[PDB]
Image (spheres, each protein chain N blue to C red):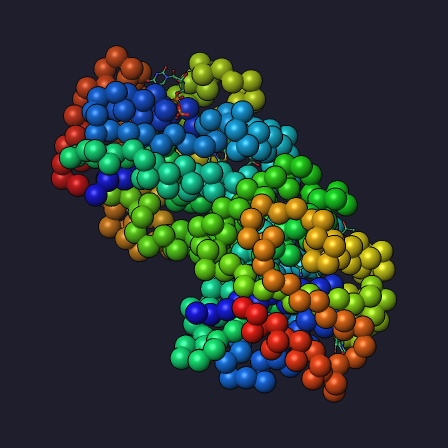
Amino acid sequence: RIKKISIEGNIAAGKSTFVNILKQLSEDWEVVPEPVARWSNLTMEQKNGGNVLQMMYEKPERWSFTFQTYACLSRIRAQLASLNGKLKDAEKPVLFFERSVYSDRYIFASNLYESESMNETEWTIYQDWHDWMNNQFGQSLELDGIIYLQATPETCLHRIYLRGRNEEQGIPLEYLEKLHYKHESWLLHRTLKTNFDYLQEVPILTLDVNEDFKDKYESLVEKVKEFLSTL
Amino acid sequence: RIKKISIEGNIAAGKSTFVNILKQLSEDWEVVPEPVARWSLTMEQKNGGNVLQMMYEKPERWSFTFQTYACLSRIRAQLASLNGKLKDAEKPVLFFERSVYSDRYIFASNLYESESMNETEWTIYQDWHDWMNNQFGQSLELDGIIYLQATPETCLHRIYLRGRNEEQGIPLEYLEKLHYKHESWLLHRTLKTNFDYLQEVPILTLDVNEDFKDKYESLVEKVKEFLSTL
Ligand SMILES: CCCc1sc(-c2ccc(OC)c(OCC(C)(C)O)c2)nc1CSc1nc(N)cc(N)n1
Ligand SMILES: CCCc1sc(-c2ccc(OC)c(OCC(C)(C)O)c2)nc1CSc1nc(N)cc(N)n1
Ligand SMILES: O=c1ccn([C@@H]2O[C@H](COP(=O)(O)OP(=O)(O)O)[C@@H](O)[C@H]2O)c(=O)[nH]1
Ligand SMILES: O=c1ccn([C@@H]2O[C@H](COP(=O)(O)OP(=O)(O)O)[C@@H](O)[C@H]2O)c(=O)[nH]1
């Protein structure tokens, strides 16, 4: 009954920008922000997240496992909070997830493994914790489609600056570049393996956000509604 | 309708010996051994083996990782046992070697108070513990608690008797912090926990300093008396 769609793409692709647009265009469309971003902006999770995000910045090799488990936990909790708690009588409800437990694992957590910020026991413990965390409480979270917002590392870095997050200025081009390749590989080229069978068959839509869209977004929105009707 | 009874106590106090003894006595009696005991070649066992050793070498690096995985591996070992064992019993009893409350209020609380987890790691751990252990409604929730009470020197002896290489380092000192906390939780029933029904969980304390492998009958008579009131 509630169709669930994941918005995916690089740091500063413009995911929050696109969802802040989309949610206003129908009373039947709602959105779940990624908790990591709310942490980059105050309850105890707000409290915990600021600290662990600031720690993760300072010493990623120490804090990656802890940050990753806590970002995923927070995301799973919140996707439930919106999902059992919003869009109650809507006629054609769609909830749009700002990223997903799949980008937590097969993009960001995996990349932290590959750049040696987690060891094989951390990675493997995380993979077990993920599998299980999502199986136990995460089942109503199966994805109906994904929208990949594809954008260059260069735009992304430029967009980081336009946001002005002082904590974020030091994030370098080559980091944006490897995530770009983790995304291109999973959602465009489709090399990336996963332990979730249905991620093979789930519909993906790819959108170029290279050009600004803040005052020019109608074609983007048409590709969405069109895509939704295939589901 | 399966009864859930946790067996609480200090390191090498006699939990695993006792639990094996109860399993032998009734066809309605089964055990859930504690995950970390078994780490002490499944995918859980490799990780478990590794993180335990990393904990023994540098606790203030690995305490958070350790506590998280220890509790997860427990929740899933317990969840599974409800889901196979004891379908065919009239008087079914599931004895757990330690509990989730054990994990958090004996061990995790101790590591943080002893500065091996910082504040963030401790509030993140507790957040997660609180969120998940409260998704399960009434499922792993205990019918009662059985506390095998020894002294630290008792526990030290038995650690030497038991003879695993890496425990041979455990200083009497640690066992002492681990004892005080079992008392505030179970005996004086001081501890304020986040789990309501647990304040209405009845407790059986057994004095277990006397070697009891040959003379457990008196202890087991009490367990029976307790299970019948329960
Ligand atoms: C964009 C703010 C979150 C951060 S901070 C960060 C980071 C920060 C500092 C770093 O070194 C100085 C760093 O280096 C990582 C690496 C060099 C690949 O080891 C990554 N990566 C990330 C992305 S990891 C991640 N995982 C999630 N599951 C969700 C999410 N939003 N982000
Ligand atoms: C018996 C094997 C588990 C270990 S290993 C360990 C440990 C090992 C070496 C240590 O010093 C280098 C150590 O120091 C702790 C301290 C002195 C308070 O920093 C603790 N504590 C423990 C007990 S923590 C724990 N948490 C659980 N959740 C369950 C359980 N059985 N034990
Ligand atoms: O068409 C656009 C798309 C994005 N942005 C800016 O680019 C940055 C990155 O976007 P956002 O924070 O939404 O990115 P996300 O990381 O959420 O994908 C922000 O400063 C946006 O205001 C913009 O000015 N015009
Ligand atoms: O009354 C007892 C109970 C235990 N043991 C021995 O002491 C060690 C520690 O016991 P156990 O493994 O049950 O302790 P736990 O860690 O489970 O509390 C084992 O080698 C037992 O054989 C003993 O000699 N007398």
